[PDB]
Image (cartoon, rainbow over all chains, first blue to last red):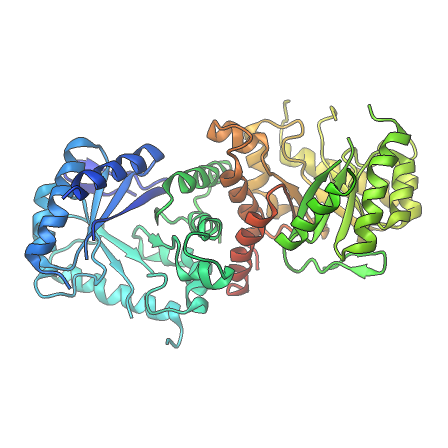
Length: 256
Length: 256
């Protein structure tokens, strides 16, 4: 399983760590330093997000960071934006993945992302009757909605959306059955770092959630999750390195 | 699945974190106080050529202090028969010998105590395997009969693959990837992977920077139904296995 963008490929046969880069001045250089740390720590992908905010107020916070990382480093760039103009601008700047939090449901965003030809990540968004069935239902509706706009299935990513409209029970039901989402034949991206799953369960502050976030990242990687979006890249890369050695000695790709 | 000793029972339906208490005699009581508050259910005591009179002086006043004050289970890592018969008299619950009671008189001494005994696979020095999983499986069948033919029932037996003891990095992850397959003996599984060479040689890190990899091994083992996890860092392990519990609970309860 691969992912093609901007002439380069991303071999998703092993777990990748996605570093979080928030830009919401010296921030251009201060974010490049933060990108340099995560890349040295082992981050293959860097998620850039700067979000209300005007289209002009957002293009100036995202584009120079996308160009700087794409010109100075060799890592994939995913942009978290819902505006159709930022999506079209980021692709020409050097971005590799469109990781919209609203799944391109904004006016023109789906059409703009179809023009770029870049991979797109669909994430479940919202009480449920069966949160797994709803996330499955969300994935089927928007896979067709992207195939209608010319976006091929090969350039799609699925994200269950941990912590977005879900309580602690809904999140761990998806974490327990995360490997079951592999029937779509698409890569899985999960973001669980420093979230309320670890906070509510452990009753700790947002700075004391590394131990639980590492456990969530390992549990996800043991089920074949291809991309793990974390804040603590160095600790997550070391944790996934043990998962890679375990899965290598198993021959299979995941546990079920 | 349970475990009875000294009148109290140990519910092995959920993973238990075993702290490592290596052994002025009140610092071991303080260090035990820290681990118990950190979530340690069992506390492993070890005094490592120490003579019999010196080892009895190191272990027993610590066992009595923990047995008569705290409410946690105590496991003693001794190979001397007199220490085994004396630790049970002090309040110890589990006989966790590293040599699996192969020392003179250690087998019959532990049979008189009626305490649960842990059997750990080892190369021979307190390597090359045709199939390390088959040898560990062979070591269990040989020593289970040896305990059964000495009066020790099967209900009072634990199994330990013995990570790092006469095993290279490849052998260890072959056992960690297939750890759940050791459940066919119907016996509880104890694993110790904290700060060992699996994390060091895989991450190319020193003994001080192995917590991230050790947590990954503990989570991987707990996802496969391991009942007891012997670690140095109890606080971080309790938090990590706590996410494991929430995942297995929403699953209904072992990955494979």
